[PDB]
Amino acid sequence: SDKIIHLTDDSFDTDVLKADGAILVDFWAEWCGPCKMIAPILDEIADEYQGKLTVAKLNIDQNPGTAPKYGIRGIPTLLLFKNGEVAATKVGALSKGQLKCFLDCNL
Ligand SMILES: [Cu+2]
Image (cartoon, rainbow, N blue to C red; front, top):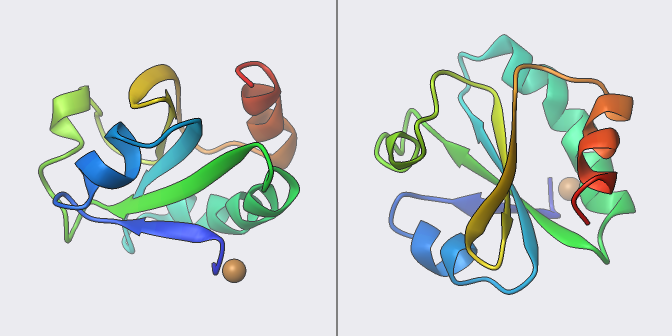
């Protein structure tokens, strides 16, 4: 969890929208079982992809406003930004194999 950027509604424009290169933003909440299931998987990808992209999470309990500006309907939802614009999204829980499948396709 040391390799994962903590986002807030206020920090978002700077950390994501203005970042150069690729960011994988994880929308999640403590009440979200399937969001917690993929947290470890996300830590390994921060690891293995450390030279390719940044991983970020935004808690929707404590930050209610950013997700609607993206039409996100419930969590987990992963958004891949490239230079502050969404390139692709993946809704629902997934496995390690499915997550790197998703990444290896847009990097
Ligand atoms: Cu860590």
